[PDB]
């Protein structure tokens, strides 16, 4: 249960090769250690299934790659023999003990509880298929509602372990049904953080942002990644989704973030960005951008998909707030503010502008940047009429279909 | 452990230290929560000059 | 399969016996379903259906990507270069 999210998190570092060499190597030593102790040999082999002849592969179990910077992934047949020994042993013994508890008769309580004990072993060794079955028998037999919440969650955690986001997706719909039927708050906190991390992994950061603020105030730690990590997820969602005012009020009215200060590199890079952004310092905004990229997105499982998406959107927001405060800027003045040369700026503005979410134009000959973004009645007009075409269209088709049938 | 065995005039002092701790970490949530505590502890009156000054 | 938003055109229509033959006719009119010619034509299986994250499999939401150029390389070259020019001024 508990060691599992540590392993998964470390392993992720070996999956990439865009992370630092010395950070990947310490992490690799750790993983081997728990391969021995916790039997994580099946997940070691799984990483090789996700490459096929992709960087991070050097395995002696199957094919190997010499363009990888990973070289600490190299299997042995000592690893493999040690596995079959341990697997065979543990399973025979532990099942035998569990079987006698089923024999002793009390249907609701004794049998149901015996069925849970299998699912912890199968979770531990990282097999999704066998875990699901044995924990399915537990849910089928009447047990307390809290337990049912625990066990559905346990299944949904194996989907983040392998990183199959869909696996998490399906199962947590079942939590949302049982959350009110159980009506328990202990585990309500946990739910908000799980479904939070689901939203984090996909492209819906609005939902995440509302769930993850709650996570800070009150935290349950079972089957959830370390609390320094939970602060790092909150700051990401807040900056991306919310704008100056909401964002600002949020990180001054969160004591939890402030009492913790910096404590790991990822947390530091995120927090730095924050201050600069609402405080209107753009000199130092830009080093922090580069820093977040390296130490926040790449290490995280759920934000490495968004590595590029993140930098893209963040340059838009910074620019938006600047454009808000100025009628005009000169390109050279706007460049000096960032700490980037004159030519450097023109490229960046010009990728955002035809897409039209920056809503400004650049007189090149005058060297000014003009801002023609409406906030009047003209702006409201643009929003509304676009939605009203959409009402027409929806009625048109559904109309036509019913008249004919 | 001293909530289970509280009979000490000495825990007014503990409460005050804690409040200072939290103030300088810059959370007011629990800076507030501890100042109330120390004040409750100083209702039964057994405090030195120094203690009330704090 | 589907076209447009999947649920908006899926609920709209179903087969009745009256309509059934008539659809078969429109497909035949075109000549082939046009999805069994495309694999023949590539001479194995595609190569550029995997070109982008949304293109690969439709399970993620849009990310509006089409260039796939990491921006971290270009930004480090920008940061360091403005700084040296200023320093040696």
Image (cartoon, coloured by chain):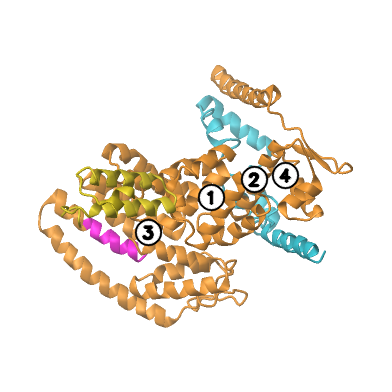
Chain colours: A orange, B yellow, C cyan
Q: Which residue is mark 4?
A: A352
Query: For the residue carrying disc 1, how many other residues have a C-alpha within 10 Å: few (<14), some (14-19), or many (20+)?
Result: many
Which label lies toward us, 2 or 1?
Answer: 2
Magenta highlight: main SS: helix
What label sits on residue A280 in the rendered view? 2
Q: The disc numbered 3 marks a residue on which chain?
A: A
Residue A388 falls left or right of residue A169? right
Q: Secondary structure at mark 3?
A: helix
Question: In the displayed image of the protein, which residue is found farthest to the bottom?
Answer: A78
In the image, residue A400 above or below residue C34: above
Q: The disc numbered 2 marks a residue on which chain?
A: A
Q: Which residue is mark 3?
A: A128
Q: How far apart in space, not on screen, are marks 2 and 1 (Cα)?
A: 19 Å
Q: How far apart in space, not on screen, are marks 4 and 1 (Cα)?
A: 21 Å
The spot of residue A351 in percent (x, y) is 74, 47
- Range of magenta residues: A115-126
The mark that comes first in sequence, 3 or 2, is: 3
Q: Badges 3 and 1: C-beta atoms under 8 Å apart?
A: no
Q: Which residue is mark 1?
A: A236
The mark that comes first in sequence, 3 or 1, is: 3
């Amino acid at each position: 249960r508990v060691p599992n999210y540590e392993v998964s998190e470390k392993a992720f570092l070996l999956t990439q090769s865009k992370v630092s060499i010395e950070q990947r190597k310490e992490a690799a030593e750790f993983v081997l250690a728990k391969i021995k102790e916790e039997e994580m040999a099946p997940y070691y082999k799984y990483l090789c299934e996700e490459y096929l002849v992709n960087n991070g592969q050097s395995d002696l179990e199957h094919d190997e790659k010499s363009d990888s910077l990973n070289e600490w992934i190299k299997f042995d047949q000592e690893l493999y023999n040690e596995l079959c020994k341990k697997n065979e042993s543990k399973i025979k013994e532990l099942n035998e003990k569990i079987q006698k508890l089923e024999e002793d008769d009390e249907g609701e309580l004794e049998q149901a509880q015996a069925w849970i004990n299998l699912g912890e072993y199968y979770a531990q060794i990282g097999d999704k298929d066998n875990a699901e079955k044995t924990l399915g028998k537990s849910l089928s037999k009447a047990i307390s509602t809290g337990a049912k919440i625990d066990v559905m969650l346990t299944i949904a955690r194996l989907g983040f372990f392998y990183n199959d986001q869909l696996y998490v997706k399906e199962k947590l719909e079942a939590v949302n049904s049982m959350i009110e039927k159980g009506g328990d708050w202990e585990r309500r906190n946990r739910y908000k953080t799980y479904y939070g991390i689901h939203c984090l992994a996909v492209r819906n950061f609005k939902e995440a942002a509302k769930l993850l603020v709650d996570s800070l105030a009150t935290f349950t730690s079972i089957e959830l990644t370390s609390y320094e990590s939970i602060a790092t997820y909150a700051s990401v969602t807040g900056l991306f989704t919310l704008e100056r005012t909401d964002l600002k009020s949020k990180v001054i009215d969160s004591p939890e973030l402030l009492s913790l200060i910096s404590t790991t590199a990822a947390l530091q890079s995120i927090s730095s960005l924050t201050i600069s952004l609402y405080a209107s310092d753009y000199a130092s905004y830009f080093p922090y951008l580069l820093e977040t990229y390296a130490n926040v997105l790449i290490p995280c499982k759920y934000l490495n998909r968004h590595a590029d998406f993140f930098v893209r959107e963040m340059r838009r927001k910074v620019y938006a707030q600047l454009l808000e405060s100025y009628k005009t800027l000169s390109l050279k003045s706007m460049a000096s503010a960032f700490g980037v040369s004159v030519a450097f700026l023109d490229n960046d503005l010009g990728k955002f502008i035809p897409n039209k979410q920056l809503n400004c134009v650049i007189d090149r000959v005058n060297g000014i940047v003009e801002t023609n973004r409406p906030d009047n009645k003209n702006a409201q007009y643009h929003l509304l009429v676009k939605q009203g075409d959409g009402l027409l269209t929806k009625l048109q088709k559904y109309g036509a279909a019913v008249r004919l049938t | 452990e001293f909530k289970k065995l509280d009979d000490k005039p000495s825990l007014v002092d503990v409460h005050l230290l804690e409040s200072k701790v939290y103030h300088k970490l810059r959370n007011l949530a629990k800076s507030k929560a501890s100042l109330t505590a120390a004040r409750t502890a100083a209702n039964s009156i057994y405090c030195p000059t120094q203690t009330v000054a704090e | 399969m589907s076209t447009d938003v999947a649920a908006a055109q899926a609920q709209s229509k179903i087969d009745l016996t009256k309509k059934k033959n008539e659809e078969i006719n429109k497909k035949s009119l075109e000549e082939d379903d046009e999805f069994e010619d495309f694999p023949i034509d590539t001479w194995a299986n595609g190569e550029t259906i995997k070109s982008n994250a949304v293109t690969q499999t439709n399970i993620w939401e849009e990310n509006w990507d089409d260039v796939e150029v990491d921006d971290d390389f270009t930004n480090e070259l920008k940061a360091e270069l403005d700084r040296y020019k200023r320093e040696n001024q």
